[PDB]
Amino acid sequence: EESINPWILTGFADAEGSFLLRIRNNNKSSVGYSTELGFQITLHNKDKSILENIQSTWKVGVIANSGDNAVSLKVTRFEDLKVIIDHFEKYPLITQKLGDYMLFKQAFCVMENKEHLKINGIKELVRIKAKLNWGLTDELKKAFPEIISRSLINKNIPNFKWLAGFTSGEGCFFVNLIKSKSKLGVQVQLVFSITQHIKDKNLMNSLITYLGCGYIKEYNKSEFSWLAFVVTKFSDINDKIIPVFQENTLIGVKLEDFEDWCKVAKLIEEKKHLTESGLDEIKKIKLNMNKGRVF
DNA sequence: CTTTCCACTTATTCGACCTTTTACCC
DNA sequence: GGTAAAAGGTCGAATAAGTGGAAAGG
Image (cartoon, rainbow, N blue to C red; front, side, top):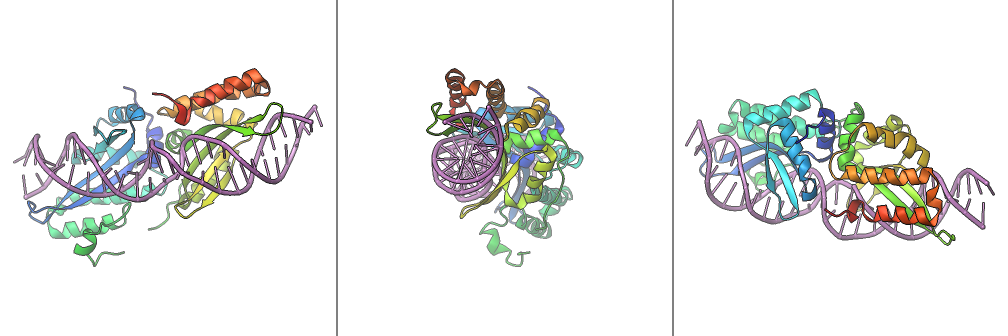
């Protein structure tokens, strides 16, 4: 088991970390409700190692299957939440998820005082939960109708370690095959992209200045609105993006995708993508990265 | 009772992907 | 005549968040 750099861990949490506050109907409870407070990450089986490493880094949490194709790390044992708070107090989140963390911290304090054992603290936890992630459930939105009433987070990228973490969840290393009527028949284009909910526009815009390259693609759709930070200029990929992740290590199978991407970059730098042979090799590498990778 | 764990589900959030247009090069 | 860069824009599933039930344990 390997230890994860704390800022890489925070970046990955900004991407995929999920805070939880269960407030459940419970007849065997003196107040009528029981609670469970925590932090979790659920991902594809192929990246179970990440969870194990996080588990090894913090020395907390339990790992369990999440259906047939996924696996989770869940931390809800109360004393162990202190580890999580100490971590994020030293290496804070910078996306809108910071808001959720804050609510989680609030909940922690309530439960630390054991106030969740009386009805007043249950009410307070419901008020906190109302602003957390998806907010109140329908059942809770019937038992507490008086509870109905979030400020934008705006924070800077702290360093490239954070970026390695975040890119491990929200980034994509892609080999694009531009098809035409040329004798070669295809233009090879490396693409780097990071994709994120439009509420974090400030952060996404800042990637352009932080990395010194790229541009934003905006998506305004019926099911979601988001931004892609994109780099397609080869000299920026080769001289800026690749060095960043060579010194700030990605986690998960995406590291392999990055390494394959770098192979193609080498071929493009040598102009071998302008030959049938090198082209065939590139197509071969592309075939087996991202969705094509075998585990 | 209360906390913690473990099997399992929902519905999001787009990563990953391909096409088409525009910009620039020899 | 080329190749490079950006823009345009889809969608299936791995996320993100949550749920049911019960053992563990104080």
